[PDB]
Amino acid sequence: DDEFLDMERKIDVTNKVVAEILSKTTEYLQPNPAYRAKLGMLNTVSKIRGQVKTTGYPQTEGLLGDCMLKYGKELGEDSTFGNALIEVGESMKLMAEVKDSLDINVKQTFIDPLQLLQDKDLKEIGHHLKKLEGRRLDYDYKKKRVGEEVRQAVEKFEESKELAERSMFNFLENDVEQVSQLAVFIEAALDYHRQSTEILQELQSKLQMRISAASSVPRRE
Amino acid sequence: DDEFLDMERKIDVTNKVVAEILSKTTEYLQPNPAYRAKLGMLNTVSKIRGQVKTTGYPQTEGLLGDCMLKYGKELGEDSTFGNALIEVGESMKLMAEVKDSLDINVKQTFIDPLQLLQDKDLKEIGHHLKKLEGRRLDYDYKKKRVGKIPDEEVRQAVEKFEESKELAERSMFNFLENDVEQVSQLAVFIEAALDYHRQSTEILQELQSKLQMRISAASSVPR
Image 1 (tube, each protein chain N blue to C red):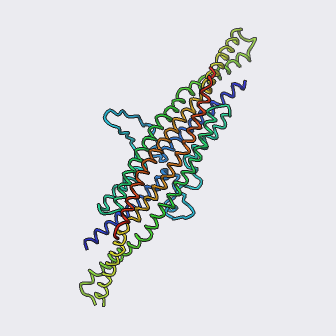
Image 2 (image 1 turned 90 degrees about the horizontal axis):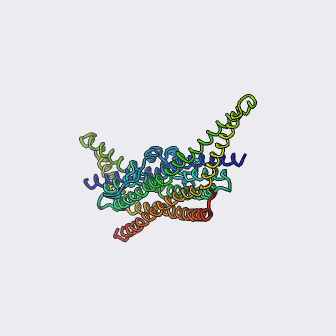
Image 3 (image 1 turned 90 degrees about the vertical axis):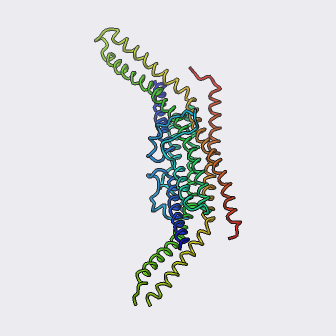
C-alpha cells in the first residue's frame, strides 16, 4: 500500500507536467494573449488545424514584413533603403510561414499527442483511482457491520485496488513513450531554426551586396 | 518645386517606416505586452567578473524549461521521463539565454540606433521645414502688401525664405543620400536574428543527440 501512494504521486506529477508543458509550449508559440486561440480551441485535437493563433493573425514576422514592403515601395525605386526594405520584408514574409509551420507542427505533432495521453491513459487511471477511493470509503464505514453488503464490498475494494495498480504500473513502465514525444518536439523546433537560418542567410547576402554596389559609388555631397 | 516636395514625401515615409519598425521589432521580440516595456530599458553589461546578461523578465523558453526541471526531479531519480525532462529543461535554459541576447542585441544595435535617427536626423529636418512654413507664410504676407511697405520689407521676406528652403532642401538631400547607412542598420538586425537562430540550432541538436541515446537505452532494456 506504500508503493501505491508512491506510484500515485508520480502519475500526479505526470499530470502536472503535461498540463504545464502544454500551456508553457502553447505560450511559447503565441506569447501574446490577444493572438493566442481560446483554450477551448487549443484544447481540441484538430488533425486539420494546427493553428494555435487567432483567425487571420499574420504572425509577428508577417506584420513586420507587410510594413517594410508597403512603405518600402512608397519610397520609390530610386531609394536604396526602400529597395532594401522590400527585400527584407520579402524575407520576413517567408519567415512567417516557417513560423506558421513551427506552430502547426508542434500543435498536431506534439501538443495533441500529449492531449490524447491526457484523455486516455490518465483519464482512465483517474477513474481507476477515483472509483477505488470511493470503493475504499464505502468499505470503511460499512466494514463495521450492516446487513451480502460487507461481502461484495471488499471484493469491490480489491478489484479497484489492483486495477489501479495495473494500469498505473503499466504506465510507469511506459515512460519512453513520453520521451519519444519530447524528441518529436525538438525535431520540429529544429527545422524552424535551420529553415529560418537559410532565409536569413539569403537575405544577409542580398543585403551585403546592395550595400557594396551602393558603397562603391561616391555618394553625392 | 516638386524636386523639393518629392524629398519631403520621402522623409515623410521614412518616419512612418522607422516608427513602424520600432513597434513591430519590439512586438517581435516580446509578443507578450508584459515585457515590451522591460525591453526598451535593456543595457549592455560590463563583464569584468563574468558574462551574465540579465534581462529582468522571463522568456517563454525559460518558463517551459523551469516546469520540466521542477517536475522532472519530482518524478524520481529512477524515472526515464523525468530524467529526460530534466535534460530537456536544461537545454531550454540555454535557449532562453540565447533569446535574451537576441532581445538585448536587437535593442542595442537596431532599436536604439533607429530611435536615434528619429531624435536627431529626422527631427532636425522636421524643424527646418517647419521653419520654412513660417518664412513662406510671412513672405506671402509682405508679398500681399507690395507698395504698402518698405523695399526691404519684401526683399528680406524672400531671402530668409530661400535661405530656408535651401536649408530644408540640403538637409533632406544628405539624409536621403546616405540611406545606404539604413540598409546597413537592417543588416545589423538580420545579423542578430541570424546569430540567434544558429546558436539555437546548435543547442537543439546537442540535445536531440542525447535524447536518441536516452530513448534507445530505454528500449534496448529487458521489459
